[PDB]
Image (cartoon, coloured by chain):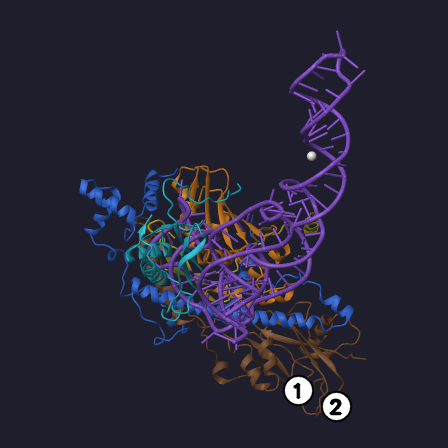
Chain colours: A yellow, B cyan, C brown, D orange, E blue, F purple
Amino acid sequence: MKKGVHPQMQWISYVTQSGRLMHVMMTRIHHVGKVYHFGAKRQLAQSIGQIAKFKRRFN
Amino acid sequence: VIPPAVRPPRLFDYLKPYVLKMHFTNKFVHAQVIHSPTATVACAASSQEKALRETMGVTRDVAAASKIGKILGERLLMKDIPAVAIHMKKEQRYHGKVKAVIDSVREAGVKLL
Amino acid sequence: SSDKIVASVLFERLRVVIPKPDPAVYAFQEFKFNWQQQFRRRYPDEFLDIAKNRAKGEYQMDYVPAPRITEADKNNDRKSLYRALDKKLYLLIFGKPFGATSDKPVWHFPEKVYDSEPTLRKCAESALKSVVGDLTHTYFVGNAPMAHMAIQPTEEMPDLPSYKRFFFKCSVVAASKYDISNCEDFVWVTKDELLEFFPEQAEFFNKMIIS
Amino acid sequence: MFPLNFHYEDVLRQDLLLKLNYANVMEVPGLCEIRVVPKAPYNFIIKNGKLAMEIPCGQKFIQTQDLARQSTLRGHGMSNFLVRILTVMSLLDFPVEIRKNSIQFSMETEFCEFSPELEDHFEIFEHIRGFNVTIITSANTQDETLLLWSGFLQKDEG
Amino acid sequence: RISDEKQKLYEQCLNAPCPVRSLTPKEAEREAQREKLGLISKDKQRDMEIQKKGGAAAMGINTDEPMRIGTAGLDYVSLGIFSADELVKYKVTAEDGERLAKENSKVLMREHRERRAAETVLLNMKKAAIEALPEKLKMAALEPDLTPFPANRGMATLTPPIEGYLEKVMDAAKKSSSKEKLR
RNA sequence: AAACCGGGCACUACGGUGAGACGUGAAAACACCCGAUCCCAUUCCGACCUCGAUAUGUGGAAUCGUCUUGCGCCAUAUGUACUGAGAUUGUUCGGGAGACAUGGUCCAAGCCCGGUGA
Ligand SMILES: [Mg+2]
């Protein structure tokens, strides 16, 4: 790595969905390091079929 | 591309028969002075030698190569070779261990041709 | 003639947490980060004020991490998949193995004598099935045995027939509790505790289990 | 010390020895480099395109003759980048493609939308098509690469 | 649209200064010759502007107080991986740097050699185990395993999982995904 | 001490340069496996090179061997083309390819340092 050429780095903390802590490096864009929690934001989308749409009405 | 075979430097006016060749491994350092007409080893100094591999701790680094260069320069000056001509291989530049050996020989007092 | 080979299973729980690093390694990593910070571009405070303008107070919830030392560790509670987090745990049962030195129970791994299966693989999943009931939270690795032990008669014991024992490897996927049957007793022990329980096979299991 | 390479050395190497036929312990595939290259139609001029590459990579890119931009990541920087992308991978179902010895991933703006550290300063990454991320492995077989990626992609959901 | 003041900020970020300006000795002599002639480059002007308002310490660099790995209150001592007595003390200098690098190289080399030797013994023993089998039982066990790894096996990290966390997150996710969203 | 083995220089296309299969790391040697703090490397990156580290792991990449072989290279035909001198309007005397065909990939071998032998 050359000198005077790359951005500065910073340490931030990750918390997994089970509460596990993990330390990583990241390009310094904040004053102090933070802790980011991960959720279950999977956001899976489903669409109903035509026979399902028919049965939702005419039964 | 196909790399062509290396030739020794061209004869111009005078012979200059003593050629200094260096070699470095993972464990030791070696330096040789070759007499070109007879294809023999006029002089040698290496950290693999029986009288040298126990008198120094580290046998592989820049300090070891500098000590080997100093020993080789004093051996050449007592075997009466006042000047040597340096040969550099395919990947050697004037840097690090090569630089240490050359500067140690020059400070020992051998002229460089 | 030479037959009645047995398939045993090595049931493991992997490490939950990372072991303690070497202090020299930790010191060098910290020093390397702090030294390399000197020669790198420092972003302006107007650029960091984009995130400083996004400074706010929510319903504050403070995060407290779980301790690496567990109540099972400090109470020496065996039969638990919550103790010895930074090491590996291995399943040992208590009962009668195929060896018939005596009637008395002795610690051993789950196993089965091979009769008609295509694979000792298929023998070993049945051998683990007969112990833990079901095979949903397990992962068997490899179609080949990780080690073998050939038992021959010696001068003190000429009665048992010659037989081989082949070890296969299986891992806990997600469960922290199991219904262990077809045995008197069970335990979750480490490599060193396994060597303490087995004085006679320590040389073999030291090479077979990687610490 | 670090979770990703520690997990590789302690869990995946033994199981990859046991699962396949190997003559030596040096024949096990590993992890070489990560190559990130921006998607084709872009501006070459705006500072957003340069900053939106410098920020998630952590190192300066190369701009060759201005028609090509590239960053290559090796070592602990590559490990930090990989453990970031594998953690943010668990919030969606991003598709990847397994080649003969490497993994291809598509770094869209919908990735940095879900990156929790890049929720702020999002106007840098807005109006950017995205990047192409390459993960080079020392794998002889596409099935070795598939096994290695299935080992590395872990979550606590399911 | 796209603010030109915002782009003027981003060019400052891309040309951001450094706490200490390192010069190759082939460039330091060019700088000294320029200073003899009386010419000041713009980067040297920015450096002297830095040094008349402070310096390396003004941008959070200290040699006596190193910045620890991790965020505030979540360092290795706070988590309990290390005690405060088994931490090696140093400063941010080159003299500590050589010694720390050499010790790190020795320790990492020995650990790597131990892991490779253990794997070699295990592989040799597996190769010996496959050859003491009957014929069809051996041809069955020469087949490579190509079943992918389970996605539900965990990965090691610095903290064991909280007991009342994962099920809570699942319950919140299913309470959100309950009912249907209006179109 | 005289043989053998490893490294460097020197000799060389029958000694070159590719491909395949089988092996080999001698208590020694070579290389890899590990790291990027100073030197150096990168118009980004320890990829290449460089600098440090390795009571013993591996010969997966290279390096050493053994055979099979493909181009080359060396040696040699038989015949023809062509050609020097000479006019029986070339009836004589000389030279002799290319492409085919046949075989080989030899023999000999110097200096220094280290190890086993001693
Ligand atoms: Mg001919």
In this rendering, the answer to whether E129 lies above or below C53 is: below
Give the amino acid type for the residue marked by disc 2 in the picture. Answer: Pro
Q: Residue at x 48, y 70 (%)?
A: E111
Quarter occupied by the C terminus of chain C: bottom right
Asked if one can make out residue C6 in the rendered structure from this viewpoint, the answer is: yes
- Residue D12 disc label: none
Q: Residue at x 45, y 67 (%)?
A: E108
Q: Residue at x 28, y 58 (%)?
A: E60
Q: In what element is the residue under mark 2?
A: loop
Decide which of A29, E176 is in the foreground and name it: A29
Q: Chain of mark 2?
A: C
Q: Which residue is mark 1?
A: C184
Q: In what element is the residue under mark 1?
A: loop
Q: CA distance from mark 1 to mark 2?
A: 29 Å
In this rendering, the answer to whether C184 lies above or below C14 is: below
Residue C34, located in which quarter of the rendered image? bottom left
- Residue C158 disc label: 2
Residue C99, located in which quarter of the rendered image? bottom right
Give the amino acid type for the residue marked by disc 1 in the picture. Answer: Glu
How far across and down, in percent of the image, does residue C102 sit? 70, 92
